[PDB]
Image (cartoon, rainbow, N blue to C red; front, side, top):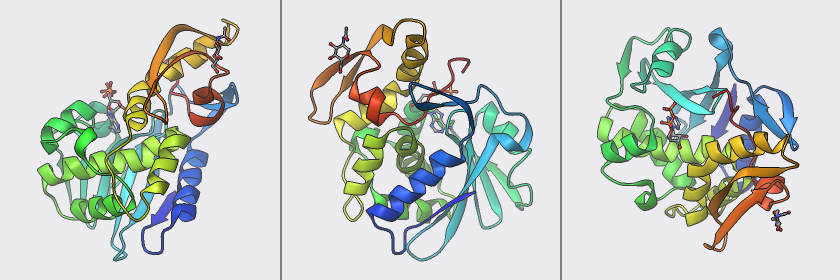
Length: 245
Ligand SMILES: Nc1ncnc2c1ncn2[C@@H]1O[C@H](COP(=O)(O)OP(=O)(O)O)[C@@H](O)[C@H]1O
Ligand SMILES: *[C@@H]1O[C@H](CO)[C@@H](O)[C@H](O)[C@H]1NC(C)=O
């Protein structure tokens, strides 16, 4: 399992949690020095448990699919909550079995779907460590509209930070003050699958992308990624989604 405590959290402790999260995800190999997530994991081993504590010491346990860093669901006290998607229904056979009831949320974990359910796009939802304290507090007691926003904050501050060093650093900057995501943050989230595919295909194409990827850089400017010598590949991306997925 991995843990993060918002009480006494600072940029260093958040960075330690994200390092813990990345290191709990299994890989058999690296592509251009980046861990390659497994194509598949059978049974309970497919799920990682993340224990998150708000400033007040109240806790949720979040279940994460180690193939893609997707959040399946979470446990608050004696109630489990799962996204409305087949992988989450399967997860509910393995995790949070002892919960008194299991609520299926009225949406999948798809960003477009969560944004419709929250009533706001990611572009307008502040993120940061105080936002994560709020999100844990929201998820402790069911409110599906409130939960959609909380889950967009939770996914970006856990899974997306694990996938990109830049997003980790953006949340560290927001340790004590929330701010809507940077243009480069939204770009990287939207491009993880694409970048993962192009990095794996660059094995066999001399480190050249078969299809260049258009990103936003840390200054807010267009950068076109054509090959593996780019900073996005050498420093930023930390996990590759397997092209089998
Ligand atoms: N359960 C989930 N948890 C976290 N992020 C998710 C989840 N489901 C979808 N996403 C995100 O939403 C976007 C679209 O994903 P998507 O193509 O819908 O995957 P899938 O088809 O398996 O649901 C991606 O940015 C993706 O990372
Ligand atoms: C490869 O990507 C880098 C980005 O750092 C760029 O400088 C270079 O022009 C690209 N193309 C080739 C052919 O290396």
